[PDB]
Image (cartoon, rainbow, N blue to C red):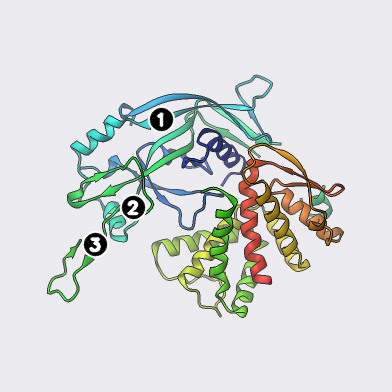
Amino acid sequence: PMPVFEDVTRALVRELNPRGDLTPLDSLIDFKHFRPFCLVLRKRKSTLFWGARYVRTDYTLLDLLEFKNMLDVQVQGLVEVPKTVKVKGTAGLSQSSTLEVQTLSVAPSALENLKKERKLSADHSFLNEMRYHEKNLYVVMEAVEAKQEVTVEQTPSLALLGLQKAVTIPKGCVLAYRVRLLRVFLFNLWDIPYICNDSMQTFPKIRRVPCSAFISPTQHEDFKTLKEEVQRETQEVEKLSPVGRSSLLTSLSHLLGKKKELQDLEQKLEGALDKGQKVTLEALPKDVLLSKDAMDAILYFLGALTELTEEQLKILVKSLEKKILPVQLKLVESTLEQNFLQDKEGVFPLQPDLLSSLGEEELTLTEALVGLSGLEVQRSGPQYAWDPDTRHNLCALYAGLSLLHLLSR
């Protein structure tokens, strides 16, 4: 996950496809696997409000059957980068606030023709595994790409606390992509429905017949939604014993100070739940037994916490110790709700009561914490500045706080 790249692509998606299903790419390390015809899987416990939504596979649609000539290219002109990001490479010694992008899309006729000419392989190992596990397969039908190579980069309290980037986007780099669900039927017939449904699945339910002599198998992106999502996962975690919550909080407490081990727990947990094996993880409380829904909620929140910087995580530990999580959570939630759909930057008065209970150190911790998620607070007013293009960072923080609050209540 690259901070500046994710900022650019999320802003880009907001501009190009407002209230649409266009997926912003959170990192460019593997952008080639989000080109048209590529197959991707839904990321477990993923969310619209931050992070990746799909993950790569080693295969394209074409790999499953028994490039350029099948793609349409349309230049799409300019998109603006976040106000904190500067673009170099296309304006001389100076800079620019815009990127030139173009879209590559599967040709309609190519898809119809493929459906006419080719069945899915019956011998493909990957396809058979996905089918057995009934995993949904998605095909990239459209990708937004950088027209030319550019470089982009980002532009008090941390000093007091005694605590505390640029990226080259290659020509043709995938910035955003649109998927559609693959559907598979009898005899390896298939299609890719234009209007994708949420009740839809890639594979039919295939069961072995009970009491048989035979073994053959046969046939919204608003604040309210975020609040409800976080609420569901916290509902999951809340079902532990107070002692259980305490134990988990201890483990997590250990991990927040070390981001790499946090990311390690996240990835190992993700692999465990996804592959479906047994979950024998050190970093989790060995005195509490974790139901799968619980581990999934934990995975969700780990996803939120890993969006935050290392300093933010340390600050979370300190804030836990100072017992100021309720206040921070209140500030974040109130600002998020009040400004969620605001498309432009703004300066606003802050409710004085929101900060009035905090001593010097507590206030400085809070200012740094929310400041690092793009929420600039000025204490003299008090005022705050809203930056829409860092909303995802604030969302993560919200989620992150929501868990920690619950565990320390």
- The location of residue 110, given as percent across then percent down, is 27, 31
Q: Position of residue 119 (x, y in %)?
A: 20, 43
**What amino acid type is highlighted by mark number 1?**
Leu
Q: Which corner quadrant holds the C terminus?
A: bottom right
Question: Is 281 located above or below residue 313 in the figure?
Answer: below
Labels 3 & 2 near each other (Cβ < 8 A): no
What is the three-letter code of the residue carrying label 2? Met
Which one is in front, 184 or 20?
20
Under circle 2, the secondary element is: loop
- Residue 229 percent across, percent down from the top left: 54, 59
Residue farthest along the top direction in this orientation: 92
Q: Nearer the viewer, mark 3 or mark 2?
A: 2
At x 54% / y 27%, what residue is drawn?
A: 149
**Snapshot quadrant of residue 177:** top left
- For residue 268, above or below residue 1: below
Q: CA distance from mark 3 to mark 2?
A: 15 Å
Q: Is residue 386 left or right of residue 125?
A: right
Is residue 326 found left or right of 234 in the rendered image? right
Q: Looking at numbered disc 3 in the image, what kind of residue is underneath it? A: Ile
**What residue did someone put label 2 on?**
200
Sooner in the amino-acid sequence: mark 2 or mark 1: 1
Left or right of 129: which side holds 162? right
Instruction: Identify the residue under disc 3.
Output: 206
Q: Nearer the viewer, residue 77 or 125?
A: 77
Q: Residue at x 61, y 54 (%)?
A: 396
The residue depicted at 38 percent of the width and 36 percent of the height is: 36
Nearer the viewer's eye, disc 3 or disc 1?
A: 3
User: Circle 1 is placed at which residue position?
Assistant: 104
